[PDB]
View 1 (tube, rainbow over the protein chains, first blue to last red):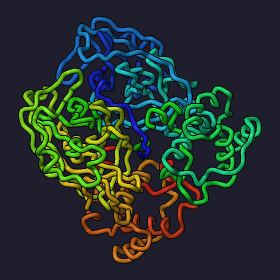
View 2: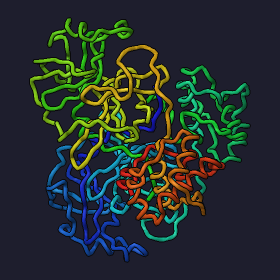
View 3: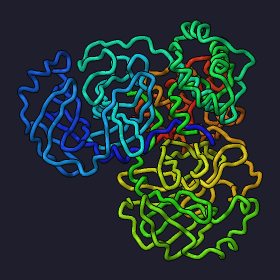
View 4: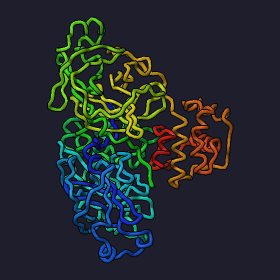
Length: 300
Length: 300
């Protein structure tokens, strides 16, 4: 079969991307029904971003200060509000290309597709993970702010992420579509720090199962181990602690491959303690943590 | 900014994917204007695939033997022909969602986006490279045959690849949209072999430039070298030989980073001769050859 990092098809979301301008500042928005969602920092200059009072900046703006452009065609703004760190611009027109959608706050370790945009135009799509420290490792130039992350199930799009900023360290922070940040981040240009980025253990195990399925299994060993003792090793290598929840989520992959979860944990232990020794697994010389168990099943 | 493997937005191509059935056999097709393009092996059983005479199999089939389904809606087949290894089914209806398009035969080392499908339904999109031996390393289950590869420029889609088969070794072969195979492959279930898979040198250099731009440059050395002497080292590590064409293509990246192409070739030489020594470049522990110079510019 083979094994690739794979985004959801982006066409349903392409139809919702718009440009929003307010002063010089232009960025991407999401047009769903008769509402445009965008980062509230569209109302800031570069000067304001050091110490913005978002109340007082927004109080200067009326409905006509916002220029929403959908391809060639401008929308009329008949209502604005701020919910947390998102701006909700009410427009005259319902989007004809609105898919079935929900807004979801995802958990760290979950994956999603990102459509990266510039002036309301999609340019690229990729699959990523929400890191344990609530950052993402993305591609976001200037003009990409308000680029969005999603999952697709049936023909329901679940919107989980809006891009707001690059932190001084070059990693990325953003909100849900209710405008709450993931992590402790704020929409201001100060020195903000993420915690230690750990590896998502359950995703690693999932990927090892994907490897076995595809015929890569040099890493399978004789040993087994315990949950308890696995976690001591996990602590030392900055792996997330594995729980019984995690074990249960791997059960289908366990069933398909004939390998018990603790036997796979023992394989991993030895890769942590000895390294990969120059060899590769599914064409990679590192342990990949950016596929959930669900993603491996979907693909397999 | 950051740096990801990034597919083109797939929405323009989603609108062209259909199911084609002929006997039991079902696979994906591409509906452009009033023509459906699909792999000619849709007319084969599993038995036929050992030694198919495609003339004689097709001669048994009339127009009504082909069941083209577009979502819920069936098309009427008013003409069939075989061009090389593709079947061209003429239909009654022009596709309303036909984008501006061309068919292009790409060269080895060029990249494209793939939309992987099942029964005329897109499920996933990823970026890949045509390898020097004309194979691709893909994700293709049963039912994915006639999944398509493309590039997008402006709003022109350039269709360059149709998936036909998995070779015994688990790599993938397919055609252009004129039905000529890339490589020496045939659409039959025999033991077929690809040549030695070499690394695409110019793509590696492009990626090193991407690394420099993003602030990863531990690998930059004091040395320089010659084209001639670089290639001797390239030969030993199964890298493609670098030409003056290649040097010229890197000139914009050279201009932006302030590093001459031969100085970068010298960096690479030392990574080949010494390895990466456990360190990473743009989060990778191997040298990536799946971004062209154009891709790095597009993204940067």
